[PDB]
Image 1 (spheres, helix red, strand yellow):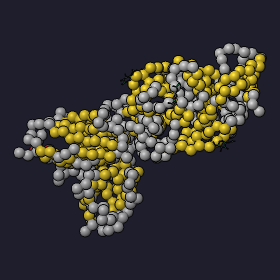
Image 2: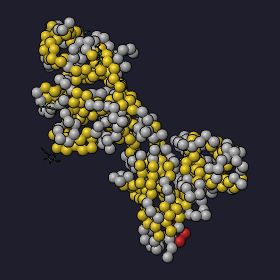
Image 3: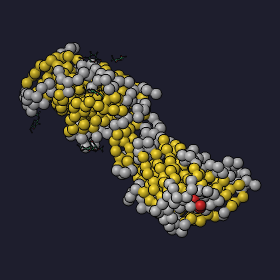
Image 4: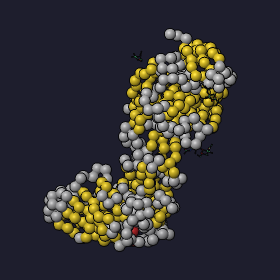
Length: 128
Length: 112
Length: 257
Ligand SMILES: *[C@@H]1O[C@H](CO)[C@@H](O[C@@H]2O[C@H](CO)[C@@H](O)[C@H](O)[C@H]2NC(C)=O)[C@H](O)[C@H]1NC(C)=O
Ligand SMILES: *[C@@H]1O[C@H](CO)[C@@H](O)[C@H](O)[C@H]1NC(C)=O
Ligand SMILES: *[C@@H]1O[C@H](CO)[C@@H](O)[C@H](O)[C@H]1NC(C)=O
Ligand SMILES: *[C@@H]1O[C@H](CO)[C@@H](O)[C@H](O)[C@H]1NC(C)=O
Ligand SMILES: *[C@@H]1O[C@H](CO)[C@@H](O)[C@H](O)[C@H]1NC(C)=O
């Protein structure tokens, strides 16, 4: 079973990078589609972006293109997320979600899409 | 972009009575693989969301048998057979066929 | 990444007259040829191993003795090769035989083998394909002194027989594939094992272990699997082989009865 653990909460003045990490266990990071989901307080949780098991690798939301970059370290099995140019609306809880990229035997397998296992949230707050 | 609608927004349910939550998609969620990818998530206050139901009606591991999924095409329902004290919180439906992945606005279920 | 996954039970069965191989590379037709070599004795006690992974260390390393008769009725993808050596760690050399769908790699290095070695297949999302990893077979492989890549000898009900000998520097492998009609896995009759490879290895081999392939689950990280195989031991024995008109060994007598 996939178990996800998180990095620490942070506060930073706008205009610098945020490093949000997610450590996987049970399954290595190359077997898993990895996604990142933002939840502002008082609002519904929305998807920032994540893996595509076919026809490309990584997709981003239309409202996060040009800010968000996601890197994957296979050696430490860690999914890092960075976004520059913080705004006061970005005070939010960030969730790393994951799924198996496929389902089935090596002879018979199909592509799987979704967010099954969710880690704990990291609170990124932007203030003075 | 696929927009999701939840119905009703807040549903006051007594203990043990079944509760029904409607999820509606403005675009048909049929994927080229054959499966349709809609998932039902439950969130408690102070807790991350966990996957109750993947692929319309299949139950995720560790999920009790009181959560059922039904419907297809553009009409989806989550039916809870028994509401207990652990069922309070906000419910979401999500799709995974067409990028970007989207979520419902959430339904709050309480006791009294 | 050494993980203990395989448990193994064993029963005992009869070899009947299996395990005969061609003792040299000389064509003989319509003759009775008596040769003294390391043969699997007739009607000998052969151990049937059932290795099960269900989704502790119960898969010990078998002795090699003077050479090994190996048999399996399983398909070509479950049993994927063998491990030979003495200490099976980084202090001594060891021989690794790994088959896959396209070819066989035979490779002698100083492997630090895992206690329960198995080749694992996993889907890679960047390569977008099921790949095979040896990181559960060994943790390192250094000072590596031999490599041999060729066409595989576990290919596609079908009984697969091998004889491994380690004689004066050469690792000799003999093999045969016999279509066995549904019944007893070790059949009656004769099927002589043709010489498959002579490898100029020159290492000490006292212990051996079978390699299995395990698949990741994607639905207790690995899918549950089973593999049944027979191990017998060669002895210095004198055989009288019958070569028919076409050069095939069609009969033999083991000279102790
Ligand atoms: C089967 O085994 C062969 C030999 O190990 C693999 O072929 C090699 O693949 C690597 C890629 O990591 C190449 O660098 C080598 O040049 C290949 N060698 C040969 C002789 O082809 C092959 O990829 C394996 N197949 C599977 C499905 O695991
Ligand atoms: C085979 O060996 C086992 C122990 O290794 C023994 O109990 C059994 O009797 C043997 N079988 C025969 C037919 O001698
Ligand atoms: C074997 O490897 C070790 C370290 O990798 C090295 O110190 C040693 O000299 C090597 N031996 C030979 C014979 O190459
Ligand atoms: C082979 O290895 C065994 C066990 O390590 C040892 O007892 C034996 O002496 C070795 N033989 C040779 C020829 O090195
Ligand atoms: C030997 O080869 C010939 C050539 O076709 C074949 O007819 C015969 O069946 C083979 N076997 C024996 C035992 O003669």
